[PDB]
Structure formats: C-alpha cells, structure tokens
Image (spheres, coloured by chain):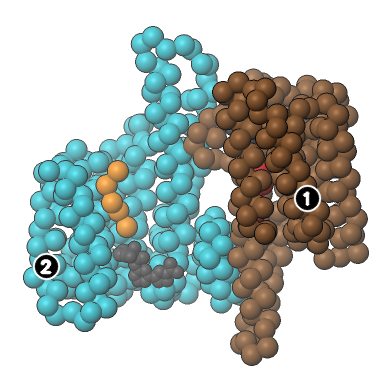
Chain colours: A red, B orange, C brown, D cyan
Amino acid sequence: FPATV
Amino acid sequence: FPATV
Amino acid sequence: GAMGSMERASLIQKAKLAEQAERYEDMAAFMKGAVEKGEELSCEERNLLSVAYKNVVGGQRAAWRVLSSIEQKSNEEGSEEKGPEVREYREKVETELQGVCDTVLGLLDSHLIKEAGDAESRVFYLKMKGDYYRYLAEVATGDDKKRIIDSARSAYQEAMDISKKEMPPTNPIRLGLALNFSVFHYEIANSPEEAISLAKTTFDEAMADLHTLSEDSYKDSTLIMQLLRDNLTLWT
Amino acid sequence: GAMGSMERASLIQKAKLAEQAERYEDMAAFMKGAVEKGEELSCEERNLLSVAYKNVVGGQRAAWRVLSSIEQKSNEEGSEEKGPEVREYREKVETELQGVCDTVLGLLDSHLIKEAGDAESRVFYLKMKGDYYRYLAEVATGDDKKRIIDSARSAYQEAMDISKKEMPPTNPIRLGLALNFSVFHYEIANSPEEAISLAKTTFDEAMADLHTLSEDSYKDSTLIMQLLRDNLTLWT
Ligand SMILES: CC(C)(Oc1ccc(Cl)cc1)C(=O)Nc1cccc(-c2csc(C(=N)N)c2)c1
Ligand SMILES: CC(C)(Oc1ccc(Cl)cc1)C(=O)Nc1cccc(-c2csc(C(=N)N)c2)c1
C-alpha cells in the first residue's frame, strides 16, 4: 500500500 | 519477561 | 455520552495514557468524549484525536483486506463452496469500520469544522473528512458509492484550496494533505496521472521552501516529503 | 449468548478467519460461542480457544504493566501530583482483564474440565486454569490474593500429576505446562529455586526422550525445550 499520514 | 506458552 | 461525566482534562490525560499502553480504541473513546465537551481543540488535541482513530480504522482496514482477499478466492472458478461465513464476517468487519468512519465524520460535522477558522485547524479537519470518506469509499459498492467518492474529493479540495492560500509549501499539514489526496487519486478515483502530478509538484515546491526553516521544522517537512517520494517510486 | 444463533461449525470457521485477520477479540468471542454449544472440543478447537484468549489477555497484561509503571512513578517521592487519572485508568484496564480471566475460568468450570477425560484435553484445560489464575494473581492485592495464587498452584499441580503419569516427557502440552508452572514459581510464588529446578529437570528428561520421536514431533518438542533453556538463561 502507499503511504498516508 | 520470561517465556510462557 | 459514556464520557459525559469525566472532566475534559481527564479525558485528554487518559487519551495520552491509552496511547502509551497501545490501547487505541480507548484513546479514541476518550478523545470522542473530549470533542463532545464542545470546546475547540488545541493542536496537540487535534493530533491525539487523529492518531487514535487512524490507528483504530487502520486495523479494521487491514482486517477487511485480509477477509476480502479470502472471499475473492472463495468465489473463484474451481474453489470449494465454503458457505456464507466469509462474506458474513467480512460484512461484520465492514459494518464496524463504517461505524467508526461515521462517528469521526459526525464529530467533524458536529461541530469541529464549522468552528475551525485558522488554517491549521480547518485544513487539518477537512483532510480528516476526506480521509474518512476515502475509507468509506474503499469498501463502497452501492447506489451511493460515487457520492462517497465525491464527498472525499470535495473535502480534500477545500482543504487544498485553503492550504495553498494560507500555508507555506513546507507546512507538514499541507504536505500530508497532498500526500493523502494523491493516494485518493491513485487508489480511489482511478487517476494515477493526477496522483503522480500532485505528489511531484508538492515535493518540488516543498524542496524550494526548505531553506526558510529551522532544523526542527526541516526535519518535520522532509519526513513527509520522503513519503511523497516513496509513493512516486512505487508508482513510476 | 450473542453467538447462540450461529452454528458451531460457523463459529469455528469464523474463529479461524478472525485469527487470519488478527482480530483476536472476535476470535475469542467466536470460540466462547463454540464452547457454549456444550460439546467437547477437538484438539484443534482447544488450541483455537487458547490462542484467542492468550492474545486478548496478553495485550491487556502489556497495557496494565505500562500503566502500573506510570502509576508507580507518579507516586514516587518528588513527583508532581497528577490526580486520580492514572490509578483510575489502570483500574479500568485491570477490571477488563479480570473480566476476561473470569470468562475463561467460567468456560473451564462450565463445563470443559469436568467432561475432559483424556490426558491431552484434561491437562490442557487445567494448564489454562492455572494460567488464568496466574494472570489474576499478577494484579491481585486484596483479602483473596493468597487464595488466587493457591488456585493457580492447585490447577497446575493437578495438571502436572496427570502429565507425569500419562504423557511422555517430550509431549508439548507437558512441556508447556512445565514451562508456565516454572514461571508461576518464579514470578508469583517467590520460589525461584523451584522454578529453576522444574525447568532444568523438564528439559533434561525431554532431552533423553527425543530419540523416540519423528522429525515433526522432534521439531515440536525442541521448540518448547528452547523456551525452557531461554528462561534458565534469564534466571542463572
Ligand atoms: C505523522 C506525523 C509525523 O506527521 C503528520 C503530518 C501531517 C498530518 Cl495532517 C498528520 C501527521 C505526525 O504525527 N505529526 C505530528 C505533528 C504535530 C504534532 C503531533 C503530535 C502531537 S501529540 C501526538 C501524539 N501522538 N500524542 C502527536 C504529530
Ligand atoms: C505455542 C505452540 C507452538 O506450542 C504449545 C505447546 C504447548 C501448549 Cl499447552 C500450547 C502451545 C503451539 O501453538 N502449539 C500447537 C500445537 C498443536 C496445535 C496447535 C494449533 C492448532 S490450530 C492453531 C491455530 N493457531 N489456529 C494452533 C498449536
């Protein structure tokens, strides 16, 4: 999965 | 801590 | 409110304790109680709220993906009929996730966003609103799926418009909003080119503003900039 | 019973799904439902039950230790009075842990142990009973603390007596029982010498029986034997 914050 | 199972 | 009888300050203190104990459902319940006291949230308190629910829903999303993968295989051509159990349990987790999202979206609508006037609060909350509609979109399949996606987009867009007018390009809230809106484009809106363009432009404009920052602000900004680069590396 | 309307087999299937999704509270609730159907449990089902509750209570114990450490520091000579919040929240976690232990002990008493006739089931359940009284003992401070400790000891002792009569020294249930009863001696009963003697004698008698085992049984037994050695290394 891609990074999110 | 010591190991338990 | 089950927290209605506890002092606001005690709820915040216990949210911090729950975090140290890795009890994120408790942390979220305590912060929901603090929000429901009706006062605006400080910067630290906004992040306690966000951290708590991001951890709770993150675990639910992880579980839902495991179960959805099992379900998809159970429905393949050649598999052995396992009965309704996998679908039922995926639906159970999905319903619990939707409930958490609805709760967070409810706090934002009643009445965190309407009282948020400063860019740092208002952008933060609108990013959250986009994030939790994004999580709803990840599991959506019904008549209102496109409306859910557009609700995420609309919230992210309002946050972006404010952030570009009122925050420097290195502001970590601006950067994290752009990171997540870029993931929205890639994973939800079927717009990989928009996702890549947003991440690249955000990274480059931040790079050019780093010279204005202290060492501590530089650390904060470059941390998020590296997540933008990580995603670009995944996508190109 | 909230699980009373679900099929036993569906509850077992969903316990396995919950495990894959790392949803151990759900796994425990499903296995509690399966136990409450009233039929004896197979070997696999006994381990699903044990795995679920060990994970749930393990997280609670970890949280309780974090909070107890914070509380102890907050009460030191020189600390700033934080108010009742740390104690209150430690008590909240403690009460939830005690509730989980009482639930497991209730399942064992109603009526898993009384219907368990084979060594592999009866020793397994009595070990569990000792384990969950041990967890109660870890947080106990009242009039009944010594009774809680003796309840753990009594359960472990009955399990040990059966295991020595009915199982080979390499049986992994016998080994795990001895591992945990040894930790009971060390951490709960203030009997480090008994803890060390039990671990050493268990290890040596297992070592001498390994020659009788297949490769797969050997792997199972040596895995637990290494935990015994690990504890001995910690204690000597
Ligand atoms: C993930 C990370 C590194 O950066 C982010 C960047 C943008 C957004 Cl919108 C969100 C996150 C972060 O968490 N940043 C951060 C910044 C400022 C205060 C706090 C904080 C205060 S109290 C607290 C606590 N966990 N008790 C955490 C945390
Ligand atoms: C921890 C470990 C390695 O050994 C133990 C040794 C003694 C005791 Cl009393 C307890 C544990 C273990 O877990 N052993 C084991 C043995 C036999 C079946 C299973 C099992 C069947 S289903 C399942 C599942 N997680 N779905 C797990 C697991």
Quarter holding the N terminus of chain D?
Answer: bottom right
In screen coordinates, is C110 left or right of C57? right
Disc on res. C197: 1
Q: Chain of mark 1?
A: C
| D168 relative to C206, above or below | below
Please give the name of the residue rendered at 65% of the width and 25% of the height, measured from the top-left corner.
C211
In screen coordinates, is D167 left or right of D137? left
Q: Quick check: is the Cβ at mark 2 less than 8 Å away from ligand 2?
A: no
- What amino acid is labelled 2 in the image? Met
Mark 1 or 2, which is nearer the eye?
1
Whole-number angstrom distance, CA of label 1 to CA of label 2:
63 Å
Q: Are marks 1 and 2 on the same chain?
A: no
Pick the residue in front: C182 or B1. Answer: C182
Disc on res. D207: 2
Pick the residue in front: C220 or C54. Answer: C220
**Residue D236 location, x and y as percent?**
12, 43
Q: Quadrant of residue C15?
A: top right
| D83 relative to C152, above or below | above
In screen coordinates, is C133 left or right of D146? right
